[PDB]
Length: 186
Ligand SMILES: OC[C@H]1O[C@@](CO)(O[C@H]2O[C@H](CO)[C@@H](O)[C@H](O)[C@H]2O)[C@@H](O)[C@@H]1O
Ligand SMILES: [Ca+2]
Ligand SMILES: [Ca+2]
Ligand SMILES: [Ca+2]
Ligand SMILES: [Ca+2]
Ligand SMILES: [Ca+2]
Ligand SMILES: [Ca+2]
Ligand SMILES: [Ca+2]
Image 1 (cartoon, rainbow, N blue to C red):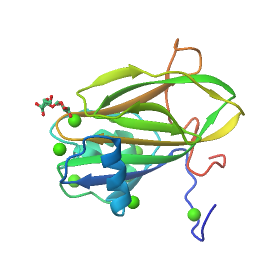
Image 2 (cartoon, rainbow, N blue to C red):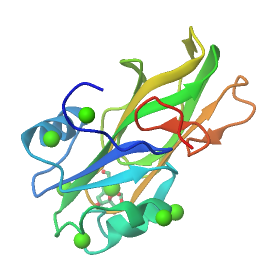
Image 3 (cartoon, rainbow, N blue to C red):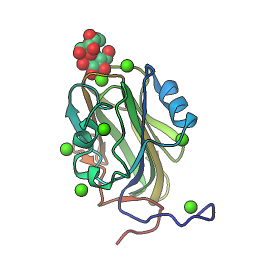
């Protein structure tokens, strides 16, 4: 806790959605959007496997469809924009050891753990899956995590999977291991 507002405890990350009518070309553009205003909607990101869909995430009900099982936690239904994206933050339970992400996305994204980038695509792209380099966790427990992802338009998908076993199996980040505050969710 770091202010005077109690924070919701749930098995997920704290999600924020931002839309814009400017072009998002890269991570910097999306982070600047996040900095520029209050979120257009908030949600609980408890099953981080979104899309795929078409015809712009920021239009109509496409965000709801993209978020799927998480859309019932939306604070509002945003109005139309051309471009948009999400900012997720909270905690993930990981034992000490080596891990790596494998992420399918359109457009780009950045994932950080304990403040260090561990999976980055700093550009727009049609759907593509990257196997990212491995990283280490020094101490078992809840690790800080954040993610950004955006859609510049067109198709959209975001599925960042994680392997604990050297790339032999991967899992989606979901309510089994996510925490919004770092306390244990029940
Ligand atoms: O290559 C850009 C070109 O492809 C289209 C096809 O619909 O968009 C694709 O590529 C974009 C990244 O440049 C993705 O954002 C998009 O989702 C994907 O459909 C066109 O919009 C543009 O012709
Ligand atoms: Ca607080
Ligand atoms: Ca903001
Ligand atoms: Ca809408
Ligand atoms: Ca879905
Ligand atoms: Ca739901
Ligand atoms: Ca655009
Ligand atoms: Ca796109």
